[PDB]
Image (cartoon, rainbow over all chains, first blue to last red; front, side, top):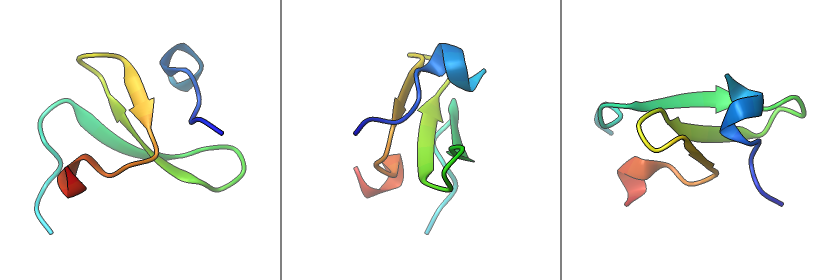
Length: 10
Length: 36
């Protein structure tokens, strides 16, 4: 898996 | 060991998994940048 998309992060 | 490089921030996702975000490049990754 990958970590969340930045634009989901912020 | 050592501060994060400028731009970087440690977070935890909604399941409890630690990741790292680089606010300059807008990339998130599991790997500690200090290990790289």
